[PDB]
């Protein structure tokens, strides 16, 4: 759920 | 480059980054991961190597984003290394390294590697 | 970290970098390759992710250096991704990507990868 | 996988590789760079990790090609690490490392990194 | 090389690999992670590029290990790319890529990168 | 607890 | 002119 | 003779 993925 | 680099870039996953290429090699801006909320905007800073070119080469550059803002603190940072190619279909082709803070026993597995291509469209 | 990161770091090849870790995640400083002349000093800029830690983890960070100064223009840039570990033997362990500006036919071979460990000694 | 992996794969640059996935994790075959001559065919050997999957995951695999045959000896070797995804549009997505034999002073710059996506079409 | 490569190598984390360098570029052997039980032994296969050298260069090589044996099936594979340097203190310096089978949404984070140095001692 | 680490 | 590129 | 090596 890392900031570098989608979404988030 | 410089002028050409300044602007908004999008990658294949939905991320967007807005950057300003300053006269003396600086790159400053914001990276936004998704949704379209302030919660996904992170600061980015990097550098580019401005060159007189007579053979169509790309402009080497790189930037870093630490994954912390007022809504999230992911304890990691990502660096993108690549080159800007301008023209009709200007793109920035990169390879990235994402490192997470780990304990020393887990250091061996703290870095992910990947690639991203960004376009103006 | 922050305080701990601020200072001079040396790697195994002879390079030195002096950095200031600013309150809100910024890293700014200079990287010097060798000899001990102004001609080997380049500007570096990066970010670090400051975290409350209760289990001895490293602090994730990254920085970029574009290889251009008033004496050299190497048409390339290097990004280092890793983590800072403090203590008696504080070190910054990193993996780096060096990309050179190429023509599109040679793009496939424009990026080198490696690792570096920096210490205060 | 296995069955699915066996066959001919092509990448975006024009290379082709023919591989046989053997019952107990082996991958054997040939890699051909271009022209359509024996002079561009090199032996490849690797392994794949066969798994019972109930959620659509890829099959992890990797292979190596040493760039020597009876017509060329490039003093280098490339390893590809990635996963096979089957289906209508089956593909093998990889990241590769190419290392050249260097002297110790140049070791720091002996490895290139990149990515390749192979398809059956 | 060849002869020189054949044997047992150890890395800084405790792993051991036993390899045979065959006359025509093949590398075959086993990799063992720890404890000293059959449960940590995995098959490895790779290639090396044998060259007439007149200037002390390393021998480029690479190998793959799929992390499955009769006791474990980690759904991943690791490839090591580097060079063999012989002599008093012969070593194999490598960079590795470890890819795990993921679903397509998680593909972006399926590969870890690192480095390892192996010695005979 | 990956086979590529210590121990296991 | 490396064997891993086009052509050669 | 790249700025990232020794010397230079």
Image (cartoon, coloured by chain):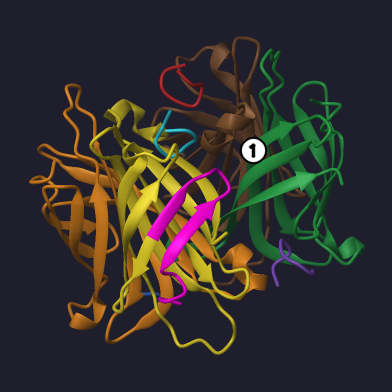
Chain colours: A red, B brown, C green, D orange, E yellow, F cyan, G blue, H purple
Secondary structure under badge 1? Answer: strand
Return the chain for callout 1.
Answer: C
Q: Is residue E42 magenta?
A: no
Q: Which residues are magenta?
A: E1-18
Residue at horizontal 72 percent and vertical 65 percent from the top:
H5
Badge count: 1
Q: Position of residue E9 (x, y in %)?
A: 48, 58
- CA neighbours of label 1 inside 10 A, class few (<14), some (14 to 19), many (20+): many
Q: Residue furthest front?
A: E36
Res. B5 visible in picture: yes
Res. B86 visible in picture: no
Q: Nearer the viewer, residue C94 or E28?
A: E28
Residue D41, compared with residue B107, is above or below; it is below
Q: Position of residue C16 (x, y in %)?
A: 83, 52
Q: Residue furthest right?
A: C37
Residue at horizontal 41 percent and vertical 37 percent from the top:
B121
Q: Is residue E13 magenta?
A: yes
Residue at horizontal 49 percent and vertical 23 percent from the top:
B33
The image quarter in which residue C48 lies: top right
Q: Quadrant of the C terminus of chain E?
A: bottom right
Residue E84, compared with residue B2, is above or below; it is below
Q: Nearer the viewer, residue C92 or D116?
A: C92
The residue beneath circle 1 is C82
The image quarter in which residue D110 lies: bottom right
Q: Position of residue C51 (x, y in %)?
A: 69, 17
Q: Position of residue C44 (x, y in %)?
A: 77, 45
Left-right relation of G6 to C19: left
């Amino acid at each position: 759920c890392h900031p570098q993925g989608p979404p988030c | 480059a410089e002028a050409g680099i300044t602007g908004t870039w999008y990658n294949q996953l939905g991320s967007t980054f807005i950057v300003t290429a300053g006269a003396d090699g600086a790159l400053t801006g914001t990276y936004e991961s998704a949704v379209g909320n302030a919660e996904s905007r992170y600061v980015l800073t990097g550098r580019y190597d401005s060159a007189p070119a007579t053979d169509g080469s790309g402009t080497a550059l790189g930037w870093t984003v630490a994954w912390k803002n007022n809504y999230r603190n992911a304890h990691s940072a990502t660096t993108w290394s690549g080159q800007y190619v301008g023209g009709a279909e200007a793109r920035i082709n990169t390879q990235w390294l994402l490192t997470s803070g780990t304990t020393e026993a887990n250091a061996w597995k703290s870095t992910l590697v990947g690639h991203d291509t960004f376009t103006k469209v």
